[PDB]
Amino acid sequence: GPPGPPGPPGPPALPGPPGPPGPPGPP
Amino acid sequence: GPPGPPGPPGPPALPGPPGPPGPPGPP
Amino acid sequence: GPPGPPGPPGPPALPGPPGPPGPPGPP
Ligand SMILES: [Zn+2]
Ligand SMILES: [Zn+2]
């Protein structure tokens, strides 16, 4: 027979990091 | 033959949006 | 046949959450 099947998809990535700080507050 | 290994890891995720605006300065 | 090859790339992940708040506005 042929080679075995391709493996499964790779591991999921993890969630990204928090975004930047928000804008400084208004005067 | 058996299945192959899992594939390559998923690509790194993106940062979130900027956070909330800060509050006003003093009156 | 032989063991199969590695699978396809893993999936992308969610972006991160909103960042920290900005600081108070100025005096
Ligand atoms: Zn064969
Ligand atoms: Zn085989």
Image (cartoon, coloured by chain):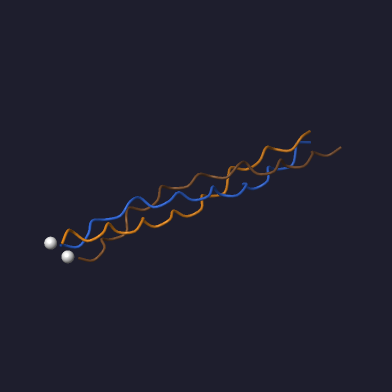
Chain colours: A orange, B brown, C blue
> In which quadrant of this rendering is ligand 1 seen?
bottom left
Name the outermost residue toward the right: B27
Quarter in which the C terminus of chain C is drawn: top right
- Residue A12 position, x and y percent, is 43, 56
Q: Which of the pair C19/C12 is nearer the observer?
A: C12
Task: Name the side, left or right, on which A17 lies relative to A22.
Answer: left
Determine the residue positioned at 33% across, 51% down: C8
Task: Name the side, left or right, on which C8 lies relative to A24.
Answer: left
Vertical arrangement, residue C3 with respect to residue A17, above or below? below
Name the outermost residue toward the top: A27
- Residue A21 position, x and y percent, is 62, 43
Name the image quarter holding residue B1: bottom left
How many tags in the picture? 0
Determine the residue positioned at 79% across, 38% down: B25
Q: Which of the pair C9/A6 is nearer the observer?
A: A6
- Residue B10 position, x and y percent, is 40, 51
- Residue C7 position, x and y percent, is 30, 55
Name the image quarter holding residue A9: bottom left
Determine the residue positioned at 49% across, 51% down: C13
Task: Name the side, left or right, on which B5 lies relative to B24.
Answer: left
Q: Which of the pair C19/B3 is nearer the observer?
A: B3
Determine the residue positioned at 67% across, 37% down: A23
Quarter in which the N terminus of chain C is drawn: bottom left
